[PDB]
Structure formats: C-alpha cells, structure tokens
Image: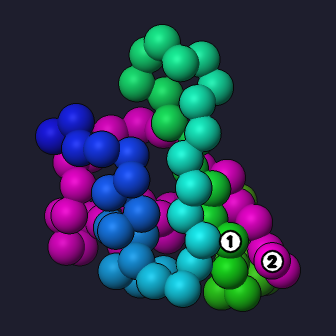
Amino acid sequence: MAISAEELEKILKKSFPSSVIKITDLVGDQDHYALEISDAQFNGLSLINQHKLVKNALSEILNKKLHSISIKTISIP
C-alpha cells in the first residue's frame, strides 16, 4: 500500500527481472506513476498484451495492490 516507486520494479522482476523498470512523474501531484519497461520479451506483442502482461505479472503473485497507472512499452534497448 503506497509502497515506494523504487519497489514497483521489484514486482515487475517476477516475470521480467532483466527488464529495465523506471518510474517518472508526469504531474507530480496525484498518484500518477509513469512505468517504463525495456527488454527483448515485449517484441511482437500488441499494446494490449504489453499493458496486460505487466498487470498479469502482479495479478498472479499479488505483490502490489491493484491500481491504475501509465505503462510505457520499450523494445530493443
């Protein structure tokens, strides 16, 4: 609950450990965290699959609570 943004990556590591997780502030006012994942596993997937995967990687282990945030997809680091 309200866990640090630096821990948000620890969760994405469950399925994407090598992946590069980074958070960025867009408004710096409300609970709006800009997630940035980079790896060679999100190649070929769709904007829906990439956005869903990140949610599934935490929907199985339930590492972090269920919230809504921006999830940017990056390939070929």
Q: Which amino acid does label 2 sit on?
A: Pro
- Which residues make up the magenta segment? 51-77
Q: Does the magenta stretch include residue 58?
A: yes
User: Quick check: 58 left or right of 34?
Assistant: left
Q: Which residue matches tag 2?
A: 77
What x and y, as percent, mark residue 25?
58, 30
User: Quick check: 33 left or right of 37?
Assistant: left
Q: What residue type is labelled 1?
A: Ser
Image-quadrant location for residue 59: bottom left
Marks 1/2: CA–CA distance: 6 Å
Q: For numbered disc 1, what is the local secondary structure?
A: strand
Which of 29/60 is in front? 29
Q: Which residue matches tag 1?
A: 38
Q: For numbered disc 2, what is the local secondary structure?
A: loop
Q: Is residue 6 magenta?
A: no
The 10 Å Cα crowd at callout 1, few under 14, some 14 to 19, many 20 or more, is: some
Is residue 48 visible in the rendered image? The answer is: no
Q: Are marks 1 and 2 in contact (CB under 8 Å)?
A: yes
N-terminal of the pair, mark 1 or mark 2, is 1
What x and y, as percent, mark residue 21?
55, 64
Image-quadrant location for residue 66: top left
